[PDB]
Amino acid sequence: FERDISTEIYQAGNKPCNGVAGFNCYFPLRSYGFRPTYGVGHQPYRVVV
Amino acid sequence: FERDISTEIYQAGNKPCNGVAGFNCYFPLRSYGFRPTYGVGHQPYRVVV
């Protein structure tokens, strides 16, 4: 039960990756993939708590 | 362990509805579509309890 909205790149090496990524540091956000041509187990559901 | 039969029209409100369609009254039955295009999502199975 906490919120986190961060666009800063999370480093995964030794050099400080404040704004440079591509060699050894990864972006912490990735996109979803929802195609109708996918399987039944790869379909998006609109879930509410 | 109670065998039951259902053909009558189900209602989702306090209005009188025994066989009336074209409204919020929903048919409580639906037809299974057994096709080879649904590998996991919809497939017949030989299940016996």
Image: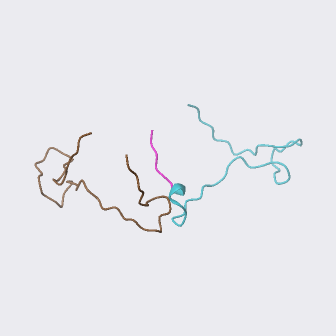
Chain colours: A cyan, B brown
Residue A32 lies in what quarter of the image? bottom right
Q: Position of residue B34 (x, y in %)?
A: 39, 65
Observer-nearest residue: B3 or A20? B3
Residue at 18% x, 61% y is B22
Residue at 83% x, 45% y is A17
As drawn, A40 above or below A11: below
Q: Position of residue A1 (x, y in %)?
A: 56, 31
Count of marks overlaid on the render: 0
Q: In the image as oriented, which residue stretches furthest toward the right?
A: A15
Q: Position of residue A47 (x, y in %)?
A: 46, 45
Residue at 19% x, 57% y is B23
Give the side of residue A41 with respect to residue B16, left or right: right
Q: Position of residue A31 (x, y in %)?
A: 63, 55
Residue at 47% x, 64% y is B38
Q: Mainly helix, strand or loop, the magenta region?
A: loop
As drawn, B33 above or below A11: below
Which quarter shows the C terminus of chain A? Answer: top left
Q: In the image as oriented, which residue stretches furthest toward the front?
A: B48
Which span of residues is magenta-colored?
A44-49
Give the side of residue A21 with respect to residue B38, left or right: right
Give the side of residue A26 with respect to residue A47, left or right: right
Observer-nearest residue: B4 or B48? B48
As drawn, B37 above or below A42: below
Give the side of residue A1 with respect to residue B11, left or right: right
* Residue B44 sits inside the magenta stretch: no
